[PDB]
Image 1 (cartoon, helix red, strand yellow):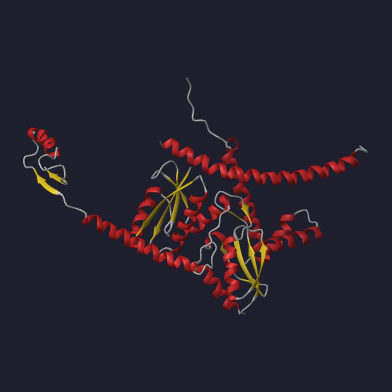
Image 2 (image 1 turned 60 degrees about the vertical axis):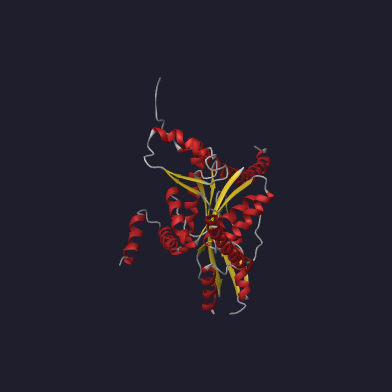
Length: 92
Length: 49
Length: 73
Length: 167
């Protein structure tokens, strides 16, 4: 619900020119969105590259490649972040 | 002019990956050094020969 | 004077060989994660292998095909 | 000396925020150079599609971002829309943009007004104009060569004449 308890799982990726690693910055935007919607979220470093998953009830439905997201800010203009918000609401 | 651009692209785009790859191999070598020291530890017991 | 278009093995170009290694690891982990989404692929083989080694028939291919064909639609 | 270009729509939030990041980088970094472009959004689609075809890139969203290898208007190497440039700046430089979304709205207005300024400036240049109009018939003739320098002397009129000539 409102103020869900949640886990986020995130996979390591090569930034342009750069090593494949776990990274947060677009995810930090997503985290900010989820927190503003009200929720408690925990972050998990999945081995599978670049990938983003969203978990509640142990049940999981999300998929993204980190680079698909907007970088930083409230992400309000990124449609995908609203799609995540919708999916969270639907999870309730 | 063409060669100048082409190789400028090549070097520029390569060198950053080269640095990242090197630092990765630094940590890979750190793992290898772990293995090498494990071998060294057993090598003490190997002195029984 | 002598002339050639020398064919290069990727090992000869550090840049290409690096790209090769990176792609290799990327694929390797891709396949791993793919099976990790589909553990059932591993699980079926594992079960067959287990009952095989319990039985230890030397024609592995007979025993496995005997398990697989009953699954066959 | 690194050289970058970014193209914008006057309304684009992320292009404006890119402008902020660019000016930050160019101010603080000795190394950094950037040139600035923006189109009216209607023009933008065509202009960018032309650029992308020439490069054989494949980018559509404003902004678009690329590094030009030697000089202004060389061949480019493509960076992605705003998130990719921010990523590049953060990782390579360590830098962070700090601007608010609300600020991006305001500056989106400011840049709309800036494009309106550009348009009015175009119109303003039309106002400045007071030439003298000259025509020459049968101009393709040997006399014409000798004549033109005497016209250009200005003594014909005084050295105070905006001259426009036709042949």
